[PDB]
Image 1 (tube, rainbow, N blue to C red):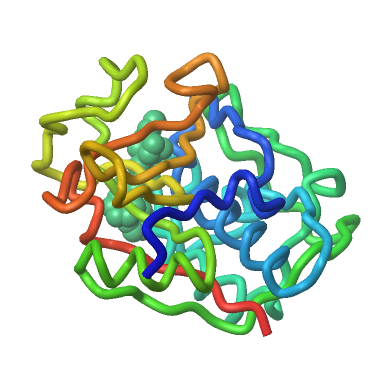
Image 2: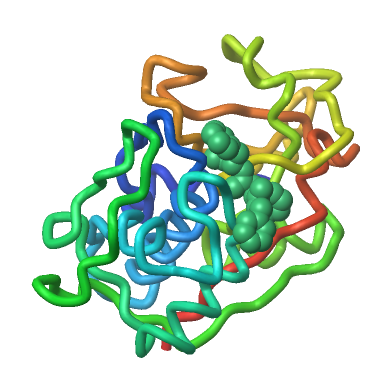
Length: 215
Ligand SMILES: O=C(N[C@@H](Cc1ccccc1)C(=O)N[C@@H](Cc1ccccc1)C(=O)CO)OCc1ccccc1
């Protein structure tokens, strides 16, 4: 694999978001992945709708939580592969509730055909990311309320609880690291990003990695 990859500088990653008081990290992870995969398939970089998942994907639990793989499966099996634009289905859950699903009045911004579940191996995830783009992952975020910048050390790695998006890595650095997009505003971390050490399963980052497939 290349020594380093950073998709943020290559036109593939939209702005950092704010999930607010809702337990919707799963939806930010899944949609951020779709956004990146759609661009890398040769389509314009488009802002897509987390609200579609939070209100309409009844195989997940709204502001009480969900799974990225369930969300990818719902899009294809129940929603004809469609992912609506942000502008046509804007985020409505920042106060912490999921309003009833709206089943018309939206415009499709992207489509997917399926998803892949990646190996539980950091070198294999990096190799896939270098060619095919950003990857949805789950982490233990319990230590992330202390992060202020730099490459974090000694991440608490006990229980997966938070969905996020891998956007790059650097194996040439003094301590090799992953680059991760969070959904806690740009005032948190490094303009909304976190770097964690790579190669020691920090925060359980290798355990639940997956991606949508765009045809
Ligand atoms: O708890 C979750 N998911 C986790 C993420 C996850 C994804 C993949 C693997 C492990 C964890 C989840 O959604 N976490 C929630 C936790 C939360 C709840 C309420 C307020 C703020 C925060 C998040 O928003 C993560 O920030 O899913 C429960 C579930 C399972 C099946 C169907 C419906 C919900």
